[PDB]
Image (tube, coloured by chain):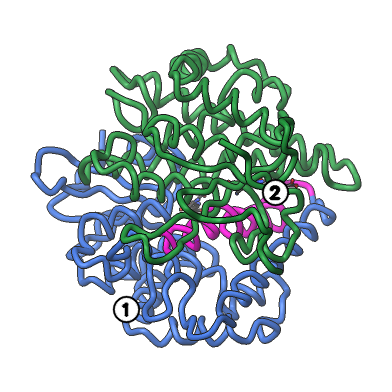
Chain colours: A blue, B green
């Protein structure tokens, strides 16, 4: 049984209470919702271990999405941050502004999106797990994961040093590849990993360029505040 | 840094390495979809993924990678990361959405189960193999935790395949690029390598056999094992 306040009249983005370490994945779909101006609700999950939530996301994490299918026949779900970006782009990015307009654009977008999904994303998550959450400290494992993060920054830096390559996938504009990468490739996160972000200057310039976008600013503000307003958990007003 | 003499792009070129039990579980993924769709393609066996010319194709310096002609045939494009090679082949060659998804509903579940593999089981399996075989020092506590995380991913797949009529991971009716991406890390041989009893996940085992019975999957496994063991060891294989 779902909570009484969980209804799907539009896209519902599932998040947790905003903290330094709880927002770096949930901010990704929120950035794209803000960029495209998609109507949406915010549901603050008290416990991702709740049986009702595992029916939405079997991996028992945020972000997750419930939405009405375009024909209204089904309730659709998206879970895994990369999948939430793919879903929003499919349903709402009509012109492929962030999803890609043609096979050539999508070939590069999917390369840099998947690189984050498979390499930096999971490496960063395992680094955080062993550094903070694992009952035993395994410094040899932590150091190897930190080393792997620097290799991923090296790859992103190489790409952004190519002539006229202002963004990761396309030269001209940011895509879901850029949105997926940003939260794990910015000064604050680099400092958490114990890295000097200035040692990747084109990657830092790129992170500031993305950070100056109004949709990205709004997304970061809102994800920090969720659960700290008038309502702590459930459907926000 | 100059491309080898025998590297030309007159059609889709799939970059692989010499076939072994632990060198084919990512390269087999695009090869399965190519065989399912009957896409014309060449095979290029890379001797050293560390070679500068190869890093210009895949900056992550791994297989699989693809070079192909653009739709209009005037330009060359690239796909790298196994999940990206599946998304590209589906975009360029699966116009009926048989494996890529025909509508927003289908693609929502395809992308959920494809991304779950790309983010969770795939990278966890890769880290497991790295610490087990490749890392200069054995870290058994790390290896054990990664092995435990694999069993959690198996539990999720088992739950999905226990749902009424859910014959495949994403769609009830047919396999998709989600199923193709998952199969190589969710079959008896790979489970045995991880030191797991695959029988503990009966619906997952039944699914792996159902996928394995497909003629395109049989052709992919037989071919990927042989790359680099034929009359030509490295470079562009003769079709
Ligand atoms: N692979 C997932 C990871 C998401 C993730 O790590 N979410 C955290 C943010 S706090 C979570 O749900 N953790 C809550 C918990 O398990 O306590 C993605 O990229 O979406
Ligand atoms: N995340 C990548 C991983 C691919 C991967 O692990 N590739 C290995 C398989 S052998 C590789 O290229 N190794 C080169 C070598 O050492 O021969 C994907 O899913 O495509």
The quadrant in which residue B145 appears is: top right
Q: Is residue A164 above or below residue A40?
A: below
B211 or A134, nearer to the observer: B211
Left or right: where does residue A14 sit relative to residue B207?
left
A74 or B90, nearer to the observer: B90
The residues bearing labels 2 and 1 have C-alpha atoms spaced at a distance of 43 Å
Residue B53 part of the magenta segment: no
Q: Position of residue A182 (x, y in %)?
A: 49, 72
The residue that label 1 is drawn on is A215
Subunit that carries the residue with mark 1: A
A39 or B33, nearer to the observer: B33
Q: Residue at horizontal 76%, vertical 53%? A: B48
Can residue A126 be seen here? The reply is yes
The quadrant in which residue B148 appears is: top right
The residue that label 2 is drawn on is B46
Q: Main secondary structure of the magenta part?
A: helix
Q: Position of residue A208 (x, y in %)?
A: 49, 86
Q: Position of residue A205 (x, y in %)?
A: 54, 87
Instruction: Give the magenta part as a residue range.
Output: A107-136
Quadrant, the C terminus of chain A: bottom left
């Amino acid at each position: 049984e779902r909570p009484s306040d969980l209804v799907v009249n539009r896209l519902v983005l599932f998040v947790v209470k905003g903290t330094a370490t709880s927002t770096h994945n949930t901010v990704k779909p929120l950035i794209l919702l803000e960029e495209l101006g998609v109507p949406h609700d915010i549901y603050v999950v008290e416990k991702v271990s709740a049986p009702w939530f595992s029916e939405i996301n079997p991996h028992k994490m945020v972000p997750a999405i419930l939405d009405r299918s375009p024909d209204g026949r089904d309730t659709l779900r998206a879970w895994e941050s990369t999948s939430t970006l793919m879903y929003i782009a499919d349903a709402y990015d009509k012109d492929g502004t962030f999803g890609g307009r043609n096979v050539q654009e999508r070939s590069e977008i999917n390369n840099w999106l998947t690189l984050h999904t498979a390499a930096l994303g999971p490496t960063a998550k395992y680094w955080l797990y062993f550094y903070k959450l694992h009952p035993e400290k395994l410094p040899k494992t932590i150091e190897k994961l930190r080393s792997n993060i620097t290799v991923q920054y090296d790859i992103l830096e190489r790409r952004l040093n190519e002539p006229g390559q202002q963004y990761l996938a396309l030269k001209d504009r940011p895509t879901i590849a850029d949105i997926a990468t940003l939260p794990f490739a910015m000064k604050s996160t680099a400092e958490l990993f114990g890295l000097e972000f200035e040692k990747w200057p084109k990657l830092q310039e790129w992170s500031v360029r993305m950070g100056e976008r109004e949709a990205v600013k709004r997304a970061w503000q809102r994800v920090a505040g969720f659960g700290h307003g008038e309502k702590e958990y459930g459907m926000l007003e």
